[PDB]
Amino acid sequence: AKAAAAAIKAIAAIIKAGGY
Amino acid sequence: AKAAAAAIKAIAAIIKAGGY
Amino acid sequence: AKAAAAAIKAIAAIIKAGGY
Amino acid sequence: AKAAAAAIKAIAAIIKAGGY
């Protein structure tokens, strides 16, 4: 469940930034 | 899609490290 | 990398619905 | 965070199938 912050909190912010 | 193998890299590795 | 706007695009909504 | 091994399990298979 560590994974289930750290990966998500990266990706849901990197999505916003990345412009996917 | 430029965001892809710039985030996904740092995610598919983090999946493994995270232990999903 | 064209795997992009199919995968993440669903997943960013599935995130919001998932309550991650 | 129980949204994890539903949406992640899709994504880690969509990665493999997608060729990111």
Image (tube, coloured by chain):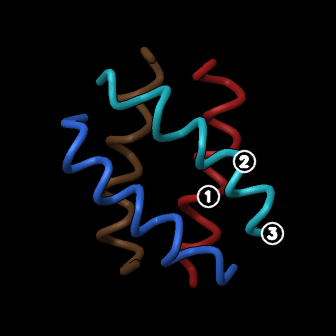
Chain colours: A red, B brown, C cyan, D blue
Q: Which mark is residue C13?
A: 2
Question: In 3D space, how far apart are the residues under numbered discs 2 and 3 (Cα atoms)?
Answer: 10 Å
Q: In this view, does D5 lie above or below C12?
A: below
**Chain letter behind tag 1:** A
Are both tags, 2 and 3, on one chain? yes
Q: Is residue B14 above or below residue D15?
A: below
Residue D8 spot, x, y in % from top left = 46, 65
Q: Does C19 sit left or right of D8 as displayed?
A: right
Residue in the picture at 58% in, 23% down:
A20
Q: Which mark is residue A8?
A: 1
Which amino acid type is marked by label 2?
Ala
Determine which quarter of the picture holds residue A7.
bottom right
Label 2, secondary structure: give it: helix
Q: Nearer the viewer, residue A10 or D1?
A: D1
Determine which quarter of the picture holds residue A5.
bottom right
Determine which quarter of the picture holds residue A14.
top right
Say few, some or many: other residues with alpha carbon within 10 Å of mark 1 (under 14 / 14 to 19 / 20 or more): some
**Chain letter behind tag 3:** C
Q: Which of marks 2 and 3 is nearer the N terminus?
A: 2
Q: In this view, does A9 lie above or below C7?
A: below
Residue B2 spot, x, y in % from top left = 42, 15
Which amino acid type is marked by label 3?
Gly
Are both tags, 1 and 3, on one chain? no
Q: Which mark is residue C19?
A: 3
Q: Which of marks 1 and 3 is in front?
A: 3
Q: Does B7 sit left or right of A10 as displayed?
A: left
Question: In 3D space, how far apart are the residues under numbered discs 1 and 2 (Cα atoms)?
Answer: 13 Å
Residue in the picture at 44% in, 36% down:
B7
Question: In 3D space, how far apart are the residues under numbered discs 1 and 3 (Cα atoms)?
Answer: 11 Å
